[PDB]
Image (cartoon, rainbow over all chains, first blue to last red; front, side):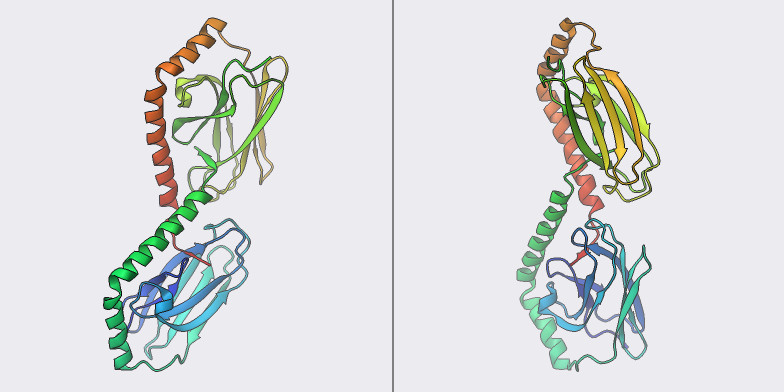
Length: 159
Length: 159
């Protein structure tokens, strides 16, 4: 038994960060650490998405939760470990843990909609159709995001 | 009663960071906040320099001291304020204070402690001589300093 479509979460700029590539044998587990997009950010919204598109919004939203109680710290400091657990029954689990505090909340997606073979084929179709339009939109967001970091590193450093 | 030469410290890459520019009317107090160049950096070294060259090593070292006990934190977090307080005589009171922990370390030096007015003009001439060599060195080092930051900000972020 395998994942019909790629799974991931929406990250800064609307980009879809893939965590489990399609046709992965289930059960499966995959982790990645993320951080806050801004200074003083007390929470992070985890939008679990499914599809093959480069931008989250163009994919199916399966579930949504918010990780509460991240102590205010500067942009990019908090270490948020996001883990995708898919059990044998193909039920999606996504936990988010602030490595520092230990604060953690998890979403269990017992039932999302129904995913038809026609829906799957269509999603794979649009992904290939809009591929270079997607690649260019993703590339631009990545530059804006990198520049945001460049503008935020205005302090001189020392050894 | 102005500063004979520019005063400052050594920062990341060996760059000379001015705190008090040349011909600044004294007495005067000037400050700047700096941070660590590496993850989990315990200390910072303050190398008080005098001259007009773009790299600290090519200038006159007036004083050197270490500020220890910076609580381990990622690159760019610790807030180390460096203060240069000059009086009428030319005595510079240099301090390095960790804005967070409150820990302070300080020295006192003589900027008026210069080896002849002939050499103040020699240093000014040494600078104008190596001005293009320096802007080449400075732009190469500053490119590495930026890349170091961009690489330290690779981690994906979330709103």
